[PDB]
Image: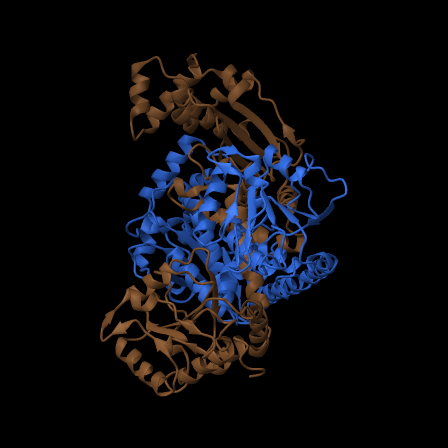
Chain colours: A brown, B blue
């Protein structure tokens, strides 16, 4: 349980660093240098997380390994502007920056543990004897070799290549961290400052952030582990928005959602001279063949009846083949509704489809009242040439090849023509 | 990263065990016996979790320590009806129950590792020499004592007190676990089996459950680590209900203030010949670049449509640079909307921004329909030269350089375009 608590403390510290950082700071979770690698414009901050709740008092031996690791990293990366930070929590130690003297560092380099001597102290303090160098270079070391190396490092006075004074002065800082509960509370209070309520943080934001940190920690690729405050904020906001929308939905019944959508669509539909394009999937509407003609007839009776006020011609695009379009054209002709399709046989014509109808107000005559065609490439290019004020999609038709920049798109979720007549304000009640 | 991934795998296994368990089962996270302790009416199930993603092939030595610990626990608790389970994942091993033979167990008891011999093998196989017993009883053991114990246990044949056959037959089971991704997917599948949705599980339920498992894991008190499926389900449902109620109720007050502000704003918006200026900061409006053109379009259809009645041109002042203004001008021209920016290249012109549009009523033509520029000093001077009737500020933009004497200032506090449309009486309901 202690290891789990330490990992949770490290995750909370990483989250606190992410929240406290600026938008220009890149922070690597489980970074190459240490647990937290904060990369600024010119200074890289490395933070090592340690949890020692079970230790009554802080001892120098408790931080031998992280200090040696940071010393070795500084020795290998002295030219880099990397600031090493040691974040350890002790229950009986005052929270704040704790100074580590050069004598303490020298005491660390004199530790009798063979593992530290072989790993970090050997590189920090190279052995002057070539025999000891060969012994340290062995991949597998016997007990006699380990004892010889330990005795040599305990008895020999070796110079330190690492600039201890410069490291402690510039590239090192030791801070006594807060408790796990205090760190969690501080992280939550940081989440207050981003505009999130207490209940929202307790229920959604904090667990989501912890899960995000844990998921980024397990990624083997270092590049994929780089995160930022803006990315986390955007992810949390997107999750909150999706949850809000989903939970606001599924509570009302079909009629209430349809009424809300109708009230949404009414203002754009009360305009006499607006251009409206429809994209319809026939398979998503029950009894499409037997009801398509009547729907268009009522649509023209409502929105294309006044010769002087209604000046724009609706365009109906269907997901079908040309032969079905010819059949619909025949049925429209039989009902005295004048439409154009742009097709002569099987060949599309740009100029026959893009033309505007002629009007004689005295005769109440319009050359054609609607455009009906299939969703071929040529038709979509024609649509792209002349953008529409409102674009309606029925049935989730793929509109990827349409250029929908600065075009008002209104998705409609229906399964019969009565619902469509309700949405387009052609019926008073379903 | 490997340890974090293993701990997450253990948490996922614990969550899966909790979900799969019945309402009468009490499950202890980080239990006394093993990581997962499932206590039924008469049988206690102990599960040990191991993660070996980095190991190509499963080896008997990979499971020496858990089997030895579990055998020692069975020896110390033989009278208890405890069914011990080992749950380890290997990438190249088939998922399912894997049998462990008595010969393999005997090989484990013959391991040469001193730690295992001193901790578990010694208790399982007591030494027949009193000297070895005294050496094993020492709290601190020297290297010579370790070597002597290792040699004695490697050379001497010792009987096994633990009933290996009965243990393997009844109280032992070894199962090859799924991968971390597969285990997470199975846990999520179990999560929707309780009546939840996939999006709800992904966003709220799974992170909350993982956080709950992690929090219960670190509790030092064993009793506080006891959990059940019913408790977790109730906690998740309560969190979901609380978040639902909060996100449904907090919007009511916001909407009431928005309605009050709308009612304050309406009286001025109904006059057909008022000059209205907008000062907007794009950073405080979501999706500004995608939706700015459409908002201006609807504003012109609402308040600058009638050529005979609408005689004042709206002015939109943005907080951007010249290049963004040029891009916006491109996008406006692409949509058949005539605006003036006062900029030719990178030079502002006073007379190009202060001119009044020409009107041909017969042709329904106005030279330009809006003024759009940036908040430069010259533009501020221009708008100060010709004062407006209503000055709307969106985003708390600094207006220190403006002459606000005898000018009606109306601060609007929004965060998206729908709220602005609702306040400006171009939407009926948000």
Nearest the camera: B161 or B205? B205
- Outermost right residue: B406
Is any atom of residue B30 visible in this view?
no
Residue A382 image offset from top left, x and y in percent: 33, 63
Residue B65 image offset from top left, x and y in percent: 40, 49
Is any atom of residue B342 visible in this view?
yes
Q: How many marks?
A: 0
- Outermost left residue: A346
Write the residue at 39% across / 23% down: A76
Residue B178 image offset from top left, x and y in percent: 37, 59
Work out whether A98 lies above or below A15: above
Would residue B254 be found to the left or right of residue B46 on screen? right
Name the quadrant of the N terminus of chain B. top left
**Quarter residue A31 falls in:** top left
Nearest the camera: A218 or B225? A218
Name the quadrant of the C terminus of chain B. bottom right
Work out whether B114 lies above or below A359: above
Nearest the camera: A157 or B150? A157
**Quarter residue A224 falls in:** top left
Work out whether B155 lies above or below B364: above
Residue A283 image offset from top left, x and y in percent: 37, 78
């Amino acid at each position: 349980d202690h290891t789990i608590k330490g990992f949770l403390y490290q995750f909370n510290k990483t989250l606190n660093s992410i929240l406290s950082s600026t938008d220009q700071d890149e922070i690597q979770i489980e970074g190459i240098i240490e647990d937290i690698d904060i990369k600024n414009s010119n200074i890289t901050n490395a933070i090592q997380c340690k949890y020692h709740e079970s230790k009554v008092r802080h001892n120098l031996s408790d931080i031998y390994k992280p200090i040696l690791q940071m010393l070795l990293h500084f020795l290998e990366n002295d030219s880099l502007n990397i600031k090493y930070a040691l974040y350890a929590y002790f229950p009986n130690e005052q929270v704040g920056v704790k100074e580590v003297t050069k004598s303490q560092i020298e005491e660390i380099l004199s530790s009798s543990n063979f593992d530290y001597i072989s790993k970090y102290i050997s590189k920090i303090k190279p052995p002057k004897e070539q025999i000891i160098k060969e012994l340290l270079g062995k991949t597998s070391k016997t007990t006699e070799d380990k004892t010889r190396i330990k005795k040599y490092y305990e008895t020999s006075k070796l110079e330190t290549i690492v600039d201890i004074d410069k490291f402690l002065r510039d590239h090192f800082v030791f801070e006594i961290g807060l408790s796990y509960e205090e760190l969690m509370n501080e992280t939550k209070n940081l989440l207050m400052k981003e505009g999130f309520s207490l209940e929202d943080v307790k229920d959604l934001f904090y667990p989501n952030s912890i899960q995000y940190i844990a998921e980024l920690s397990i990624l083997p690729e270092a590049e994929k582990r780089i995160s930022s405050k803006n990315k986390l904020i955007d992810y949390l906001k997107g999750n909150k928005k999706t949850a809000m929308s989903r939970w606001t939905s599924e509570v009302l019944t079909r009629k209430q959602l349809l009424k809300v959508r109708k009230n949404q669509l009414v203002p754009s539909l009360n305009i006499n001279s607006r251009s409206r394009y429809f994209i319809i999937d026939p398979d998503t509407i029950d009894n499409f063949d037997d009801e398509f003609i009547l729907f268009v007839k009522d649509y023209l009776d409502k929105y294309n009846s006044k010769i002087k006020l209604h000046t724009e011609t609706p365009c109906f695009i269907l997901k079908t083949d040309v032969n079905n379009l010819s059949e619909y054209h025949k049925r429209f002709v039989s009902r005295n509704i004048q439409i154009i399709t742009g097709y002569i046989g099987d060949t599309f014509y740009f100029k026959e489809f893009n033309k505007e109808p002629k009007r004689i107000i005295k005769d109440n005559w319009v050359e054609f009242k609607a455009r009906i065609s299939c969703n071929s490439d040529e038709v979509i290019k024609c649509i792209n040439y002349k953008k529409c004020d409102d674009l309606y999609i029925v049935g989730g038709v793929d509109v990827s090849l349409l250029d929908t920049a600065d075009v008002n798109i209104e998705n409609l979720e229906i399964n019969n023509f009565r619902e469509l007549k309700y949405l387009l304000s052609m019926l008073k009640e379903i």
